[PDB]
Length: 157
Ligand SMILES: CC[C@@H](C)c1nccs1
Image (cartoon, rainbow, N blue to C red; front, top):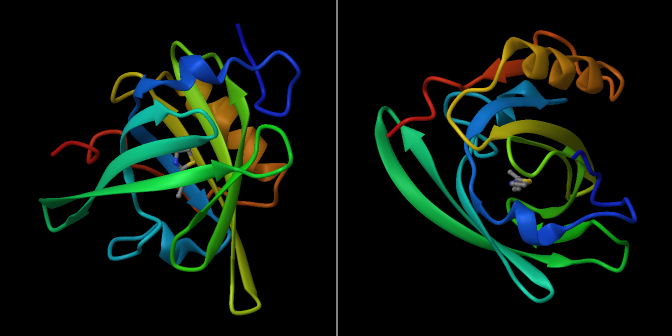
């Protein structure tokens, strides 16, 4: 079972748990890049009453650093915000709770805006079909093949 966060049938409860950064794509590649700060490796989701705790790490030349953020429930169902290098809101366009998770986020800081999508898996790697499916969704959001980065095997600390 597939579900949207927007969807009337979404069980947030099941987003809970261990997740993995498999692919990131941005509108602004630099964010996704080597010393970029949207370059985050999801570690786990702890679902809360109205919030979500996301613990991730960042990696500057193979050394990792742990970071936890609290995204909260905005008024719009399935959507949340979190304050990070400006103001961010995100949704989960697609998930199957047990294997993959796809996100869509909107960073808006100082009048400047950028789009970021990610493919997260329950395991460090997902199939080429998913990556591909994840790849056609980004194209429909205006992000090109040169803007998608597969972190599937660098996602390990
Ligand atoms: C900053 C929030 C981005 C990176 C995401 N984390 C997991 C769901 S969306």
